[PDB]
Image (cartoon, rainbow, N blue to C red; front, side, top):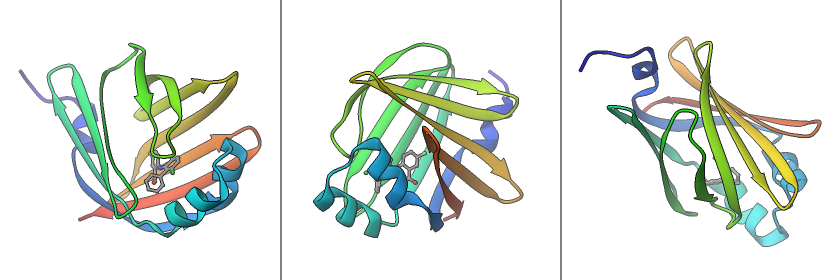
Amino acid sequence: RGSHMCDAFVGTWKLVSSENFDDYMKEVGVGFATRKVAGMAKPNMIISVNGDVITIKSESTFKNTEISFILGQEFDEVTADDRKVKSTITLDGGVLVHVQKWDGKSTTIKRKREDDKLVVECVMKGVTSTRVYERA
Ligand SMILES: O=C(O)c1cc(F)ccc1Nc1cccc(Cl)c1-c1ccccc1
């Protein structure tokens, strides 16, 4: 089994900057106490690929979470803020596009490589948050 373009995401990443994330969590519907505690967190993101299966882990003082998935195939996810969502992740021109649907709501998380960084864009309606990660 050979290399894949998405191996560019593989590695250990740490959060280095965040913008508008509190507003993004508000639009998602995250309650007060969770927003305050989660807004303080500096998560590590650990991405690995094994065959068709991509695994993304998030570790922080707030919560430790993990998702494993195959591109284009819907799965059940319990988010860090305790939402139970249906998720589908696909590869669009080098960008991992992650859509979560729940309670009639929808949010989109994009992960992309920019220079030596992994840039995350969290979009909920008209509210966007940027989370920038660097190699740990
Ligand atoms: O935290 C990131 O950067 C991130 C990146 C992603 F690609 C996808 C999700 C992310 N985090 C969250 C999304 C919604 C709600 C919450 Cl509470 C979190 C969250 C906050 C603090 C610690 C752990 C998780």
